[PDB]
Image 1 (cartoon, rainbow, N blue to C red):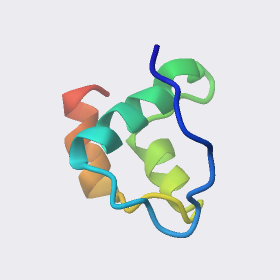
Image 2 (image 1 turned 45 degrees about the vertical axis):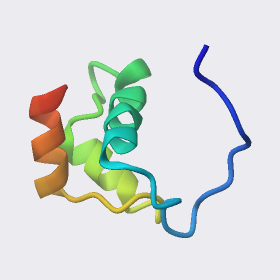
Image 3 (image 1 turned 135 degrees about the vertical axis):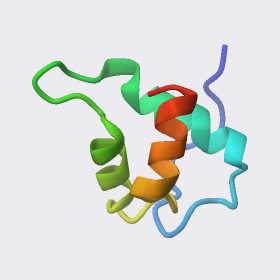
Length: 67
């Protein structure tokens, strides 16, 4: 009740909406870790994966929206 479409959007995000990114960040924290939680640093690092266009700053903002 959420999954849809395929998965293949490495080179830059699909112009996703700010709202989509939110759930995206939270989704990443869906199965975080205690000794390796998806903190703003992590999620932010994830972006380095050459996927979405985030940033410690942006993540920080989201962190508050969810964290």
